[PDB]
Image (spheres, rainbow, N blue to C red):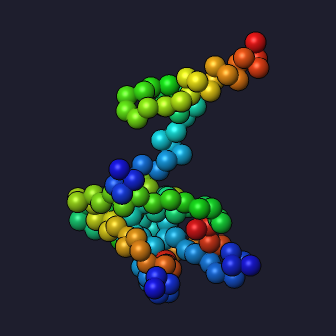
C-alpha cells in the first residue's frame, strides 16, 4: 500500500540544487547523489509531496 | 492560478558581512545575491 | 545501474543504440537473417 500522502515542509534554501528547482510547471529531475561536504542537505526521495517554505 | 496566488521572496539588498565578506546574513554569497529584518527581501511571484 | 542513476534518455543517442544493434557479445540473435530478407525486398 504505497499512497501514503506524506508532505515534506522543508526550507527553500536548506534543500540541495535550488537552481534545479527553477522552472514553472516543469518536471525537473533530481538525483539522489549525496555530497558529504555540502551544507545543502539532500532530499528524502520517497516522499510524495513537498512544500518549500 | 497557483503562481498568481502564492508568492516567493528573495532578500538581495543590504548584504551585510557575518565574519566573512562573502557570507551574507541571507545565506547566499555576495556575488550570488542579485524576512525583511536586516535582509530587505522583495516579494515576487513564484517561479518554482 | 539505474539504482545509482542512469537517467536513460541522457544515456541514449542514435549511435549508442546503433552499436547495440550490431554487437553480438552475448545471446544469439536472428537479425542477420531478418535484415537480409527485408533488403531482398529492397534489392
Evaluate whether residue A24 shows in this view: yes
Q: Report the number of discs.
A: 0
* Residue B37 in view in this figure: no
Image coordinates of residue C30 in percent, x first then y, are 53, 30
Residue A47 or B41: which is nearer the viewer? A47
Quarter occupied by residue A46: bottom left
Residue situated in front as seen by the camera: A34 or C23: C23
Above or below: residue C8 compared with residue A51: above
Q: Nearer the viewer, residue A46 or C38?
A: C38
Answer with the quarter of the image where residue B38 lies: bottom left
- Provide residue B18's location: percent of width, then percent of height: 28, 68
> What residue is drawn where x is 28% and y is 65%?
A39
Indicate the position of residue A13 as horizontal and vertical percent values: 42, 70
Q: Image point 45% across, 68% down: which residue?
A: B14
Residue depicted at 46% across the width and 85% down the height: A1
Q: Is residue A52 left or right of residue B30?
A: right
> Where's residue B37, x and y in %?
44, 82
**Residue A43 falls in image quadrant:** bottom left
Q: Nearer the viewer, residue A47 or A20?
A: A47
Amino acid at each position: 500500500r504505497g499512497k501514503i500522502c506524506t508532505i515534506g515542509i522543508a526550507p527553500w534554501g536548506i534543500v540541495e540544487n535550488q537552481e534545479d528547482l527553477i522552472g514553472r510547471d516543469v518536471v525537473r529531475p533530481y538525483q539522489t547523489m549525496s555530497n558529504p561536504m555540502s551544507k545543502l542537505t539532500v532530499l528524502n526521495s520517497m516522499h510524495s509531496h513537498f512544500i518549500l517554505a | 492560478w497557483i503562481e498568481r496566488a502564492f508568492y516567493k521572496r528573495e532578500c538581495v539588498h543590504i548584504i551585510p558581512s557575518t565574519k566573512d565578506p562573502h557570507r551574507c546574513c541571507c545565506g547566499r554569497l555576495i556575488g550570488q545575491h542579485v524576512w525583511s529584518i536586516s535582509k530587505h527581501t522583495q516579494l515576487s511571484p513564484t517561479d518554482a | 545501474l539505474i539504482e545509482n542513476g542512469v537517467s536513460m534518455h541522457r544515456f541514449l543517442t542514435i549511435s549508442r543504440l546503433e552499436e547495440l544493434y550490431n554487437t553480438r557479445h552475448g545471446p544469439s540473435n536472428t537479425l542477420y537473417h531478418l535484415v537480409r530478407d527485408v533488403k531482398k525486398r529492397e534489392y
